[PDB]
Image (cartoon, grey):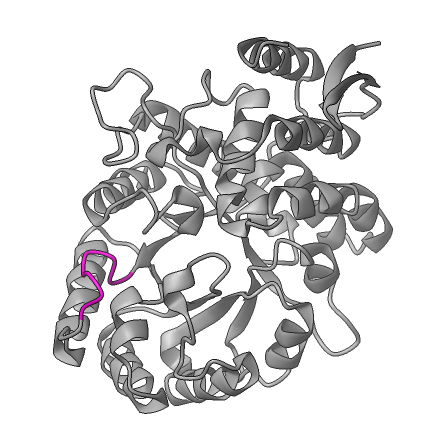
Amino acid sequence: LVSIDLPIEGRLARYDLTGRPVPFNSRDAKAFSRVAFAAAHVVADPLADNDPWLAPAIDWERTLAFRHRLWDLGLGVAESMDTAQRGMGLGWPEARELIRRSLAEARGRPDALIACGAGTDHLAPGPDVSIDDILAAYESQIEAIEAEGGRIILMASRALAAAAKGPEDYIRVYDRVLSQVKEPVIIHWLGEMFDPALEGYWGNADHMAAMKTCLDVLEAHAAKVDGIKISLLSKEKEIVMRRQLPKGVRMYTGDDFNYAELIAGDEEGHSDALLGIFDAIAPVASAALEALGSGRNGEFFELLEPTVPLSRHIFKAPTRFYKTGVVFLAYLNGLQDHFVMIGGQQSARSLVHLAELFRLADKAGALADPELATARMRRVLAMHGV
């Protein structure tokens, strides 16, 4: 019986932990009936002589240990993605290095699925940045990744969102890029709540009309496109899109609010998964993907539905700070020994939010080690003078 006093409404109240941790169990992806990636976070080095809001310092050992944890659970790894703070703390040089190390770890394992974010993030949006400049940016990163034997997740581009004079520029850019990739790609449609500089991507401010342009690209280069990850957090928009998708082009859900419903699917289809939440609830997701693969849909929901409130909390407005809840949860689970983040983002959620995160994590069976989680929460409260 573990109990802790936690902040609610300016005051402090008893919370008794009541969750049964879902036990960590090693698993092979073949036990699943879905293709599931976790977009994995980065562990900062808390001893480096960096300026924390200006430039990052990474703990490689701790960062790579977390990729192995994901591979162990059968989950794939989506590297240097939005969850690894790409474009918002993690520059291209550090992203390229993380990609390089992770690929090398992967080849060291029989069971390591991994795909690497390739984009434009080394290029500043500019009033005279050209389409050619943008193609050069994409191919530069794409070639860098392919040289390390990586499959690509094709990221949305900040410079293109600012240079594009309509839908036709997206068509041309993705036409050259996709005809020049060497292997099937997963296209990433990242919404503005995650990246405000990706405003009106595909050439329209309206998501329903931007969808049209996006669908057109996938039709045009279907063989070169393994899938699309949508991160708009609009569940109706995903369902409508996954039904219009070409033969052999997968729908990877990016919807951390609605993943359980979407992964299980409807009477028309399901979607696969490429989720930042799968990082934070890795053990549970694994256990549930196994149940789903065993046609045991009841246990799938029993395991996953309790995480859903935790997830909605972690990704709540302002949503771009979800990474804080993810790394805080890693810290509670002892996957790292500190709560220091690239960009100094440990501080982007209130204490009240971190305490609520702890309760929802408890009730979702997402605290692997409740006693350790509780001690760590206590150290965090003490630091805040509680």
198 relative to 367, above or below: below
Residue 357: quarter of image = top right
Q: Chief secondary structure of the magenta span?
A: loop
374 relative to 76, above or below: above
On the question of residue 113 being in view, the answer is: no
Residue 120: say if magenta: yes
On the question of residue 144 being in view, the answer is: yes
Residue drawn at point x = 17 percent, y = 56 percent: 144
Residue 266: image x %, image y %? 77, 71
163 relative to 87, above or below: below
Residue 224: image x %, image y %? 36, 77
Residue 238: image x %, image y %? 62, 72
Q: Is residue 5 left or right of residue 18?
A: left
Q: Is residue 132 left or right of residue 116?
A: left
Residue 360: image x %, image y %? 74, 33
Quarter of the image with the C terminus is top right
Residue 123: say if magenta: yes
Q: Which residues are magenta?
A: 119-126
Residue 214: quarter of image = bottom left
Residue drawn at point x = 38 percent, y = 89 percent: 220
- Of residues 87 and 145, the one drawn nearer to the viewer in this rendering: 87
Quarter of the image with the N terminus is top right
Q: Is residue 133 left or right of residue 152?
A: left
Query: Disc count in the image?
Result: 0
- Of residues 202 and 222, the one drawn nearer to the viewer in this rendering: 202
Residue drawn at point x = 75 percent, y = 61 percent: 261
Residue drawn at point x = 29 percent, y = 77 percent: 178
Q: Is residue 201 left or right of residue 275?
A: left
Residue 131: quarter of image = bottom left
